[PDB]
Image (cartoon, helix red, strand yellow):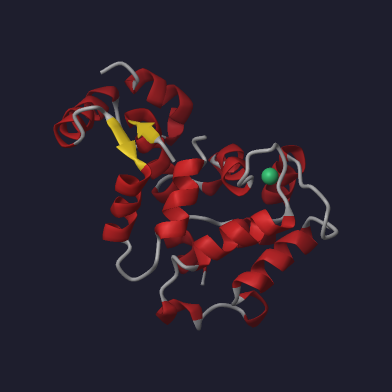
Length: 188
Ligand SMILES: [Ca+2]
């Protein structure tokens, strides 16, 4: 049951579990996935199961990739769940950058923002989308607003430094880049 203190370090005060509790979870985990590794397909299924009202395939895929297809270990699988469903968005900005930097080349492009914003948009039920502000109710509008808030040109590249600054300072950027299905819904 090693990676548990590793899980808590990389999670810190963000963890919603203790080492003894993570081990129990870990124990159940191994019963279901003996190898302790979970594939992208299996990960996607978790979200498809628990987000019946939406279409979480792309979202789950992007989340899985943020940890580098292939497989995730228990530590990543636990952290991945925390990133999407627990804690404060503010303690996840470094990870959020990893999420938005789709190809992982170190910077975020305009298209990459559209990719993630679209994936996140599909996590919203059709029902709740009518509550979205007019200038923020379609993937294109939201991604473009985000790009505008960072004052970028179509071919500009957004750095981690700037990403973190703006998501911290400009609360409208935070609202727009928001990736937690429940938080997006609640703010609406
Ligand atoms: Ca990139």
